[PDB]
Length: 128
Image (cartoon, rainbow, N blue to C red; front, side, top):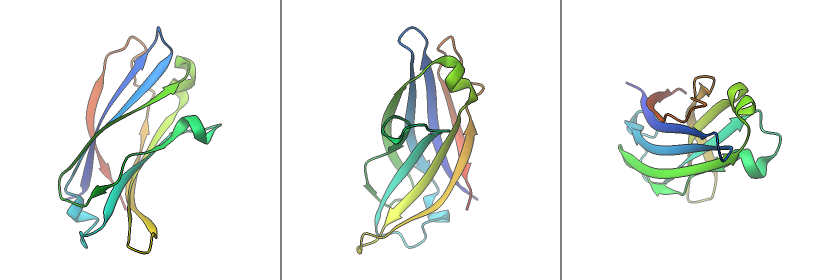
Protein backbone atom coordinates (compact mmCIF):
# COMPACT_ATOMS: atom_id res chain seq x y z
CA UNK A 1 0.00 0.00 0.00
CA UNK A 2 3.00 2.23 -0.61
CA UNK A 3 4.32 4.05 -3.65
CA UNK A 4 7.12 1.93 -5.14
CA UNK A 5 10.07 2.71 -7.42
CA UNK A 6 12.04 0.20 -9.49
CA UNK A 7 15.75 0.94 -9.91
CA UNK A 8 18.64 -0.81 -11.63
CA UNK A 9 22.21 -0.26 -10.39
CA UNK A 10 25.55 -1.14 -12.01
CA UNK A 11 29.21 -0.27 -11.54
CA UNK A 12 31.71 -0.27 -14.41
CA UNK A 13 35.02 -1.24 -12.78
CA UNK A 14 37.18 -0.80 -15.89
CA UNK A 15 35.85 2.67 -16.75
CA UNK A 16 35.36 3.63 -13.09
CA UNK A 17 31.75 4.72 -13.46
CA UNK A 18 28.53 4.05 -11.58
CA UNK A 19 25.22 3.82 -13.47
CA UNK A 20 21.85 4.58 -11.90
CA UNK A 21 18.77 3.64 -13.93
CA UNK A 22 15.54 5.14 -12.65
CA UNK A 23 13.01 2.79 -14.26
CA UNK A 24 9.43 3.32 -13.07
CA UNK A 25 7.08 4.45 -10.31
CA UNK A 26 4.14 2.28 -9.21
CA UNK A 27 1.09 3.15 -7.08
CA UNK A 28 1.97 6.85 -7.02
CA UNK A 29 -1.68 7.51 -6.18
CA UNK A 30 -0.75 6.47 -2.64
CA UNK A 31 1.28 9.69 -2.24
CA UNK A 32 0.07 12.06 -4.96
CA UNK A 33 -3.69 11.73 -4.62
CA UNK A 34 -4.31 15.10 -6.27
CA UNK A 35 -2.98 13.82 -9.63
CA UNK A 36 -2.72 16.83 -11.96
CA UNK A 37 0.81 18.24 -11.94
CA UNK A 38 4.31 17.32 -13.12
CA UNK A 39 6.35 14.73 -11.24
CA UNK A 40 10.04 13.93 -11.11
CA UNK A 41 12.49 11.77 -9.17
CA UNK A 42 15.30 13.42 -7.22
CA UNK A 43 18.39 11.21 -6.93
CA UNK A 44 21.45 11.65 -4.73
CA UNK A 45 24.59 9.58 -4.10
CA UNK A 46 25.38 10.57 -0.51
CA UNK A 47 27.61 11.85 0.87
CA UNK A 48 27.98 14.11 -2.18
CA UNK A 49 31.11 16.27 -2.11
CA UNK A 50 29.95 18.05 -5.27
CA UNK A 51 26.40 18.66 -6.50
CA UNK A 52 27.40 18.80 -10.16
CA UNK A 53 28.38 15.12 -10.19
CA UNK A 54 26.42 13.26 -7.48
CA UNK A 55 22.99 14.91 -7.39
CA UNK A 56 20.44 14.36 -10.17
CA UNK A 57 16.81 14.79 -11.11
CA UNK A 58 14.81 13.07 -13.84
CA UNK A 59 12.81 14.93 -16.45
CA UNK A 60 9.31 16.03 -15.43
CA UNK A 61 6.38 13.77 -16.34
CA UNK A 62 2.63 14.17 -15.93
CA UNK A 63 1.34 12.39 -12.83
CA UNK A 64 -0.04 8.89 -13.35
CA UNK A 65 -0.37 5.83 -11.12
CA UNK A 66 2.29 3.96 -13.10
CA UNK A 67 5.08 6.11 -14.51
CA UNK A 68 8.03 5.04 -16.66
CA UNK A 69 11.15 7.21 -16.61
CA UNK A 70 13.81 4.89 -18.02
CA UNK A 71 16.39 7.54 -17.18
CA UNK A 72 20.00 6.69 -16.45
CA UNK A 73 22.52 8.76 -14.50
CA UNK A 74 26.30 8.29 -14.42
CA UNK A 75 28.90 9.16 -11.80
CA UNK A 76 32.65 8.75 -12.28
CA UNK A 77 33.86 7.27 -9.01
CA UNK A 78 36.02 4.54 -7.52
CA UNK A 79 34.56 1.34 -6.12
CA UNK A 80 35.71 2.05 -2.53
CA UNK A 81 33.95 5.41 -2.85
CA UNK A 82 30.74 3.83 -4.16
CA UNK A 83 30.82 1.10 -1.53
CA UNK A 84 30.42 3.61 1.30
CA UNK A 85 27.63 5.59 -0.39
CA UNK A 86 23.89 5.77 0.18
CA UNK A 87 21.42 6.40 -2.63
CA UNK A 88 18.66 8.84 -1.70
CA UNK A 89 15.58 8.93 -3.94
CA UNK A 90 12.52 11.17 -3.61
CA UNK A 91 9.44 11.63 -5.75
CA UNK A 92 8.59 15.32 -5.97
CA UNK A 93 5.92 17.37 -7.79
CA UNK A 94 5.54 21.01 -8.85
CA UNK A 95 2.25 22.93 -8.84
CA UNK A 96 1.28 25.66 -11.30
CA UNK A 97 2.96 28.28 -9.10
CA UNK A 98 6.31 26.47 -9.54
CA UNK A 99 6.25 25.34 -5.92
CA UNK A 100 7.90 21.97 -5.40
CA UNK A 101 7.04 19.40 -2.77
CA UNK A 102 8.64 16.01 -2.27
CA UNK A 103 6.07 13.48 -1.10
CA UNK A 104 8.27 10.56 -0.10
CA UNK A 105 11.46 8.64 -0.67
CA UNK A 106 13.90 6.01 0.47
CA UNK A 107 17.55 5.61 1.43
CA UNK A 108 19.20 2.74 -0.39
CA UNK A 109 22.51 1.28 0.72
CA UNK A 110 24.95 0.77 -2.14
CA UNK A 111 27.21 -1.60 -0.17
CA UNK A 112 25.79 -4.55 -2.13
CA UNK A 113 26.50 -3.15 -5.60
CA UNK A 114 28.84 -5.58 -7.38
CA UNK A 115 32.37 -4.41 -8.17
CA UNK A 116 32.36 -7.14 -10.86
CA UNK A 117 29.60 -5.40 -12.80
CA UNK A 118 26.45 -7.49 -12.32
CA UNK A 119 23.36 -5.29 -12.62
CA UNK A 120 20.82 -5.30 -9.79
CA UNK A 121 17.16 -4.49 -10.45
CA UNK A 122 14.93 -4.07 -7.41
CA UNK A 123 11.83 -2.32 -6.11
CA UNK A 124 11.90 0.08 -3.16
CA UNK A 125 9.04 1.59 -1.16
CA UNK A 126 8.99 5.38 -0.93
CA UNK A 127 7.91 6.39 2.57
CA UNK A 128 6.33 9.65 3.68
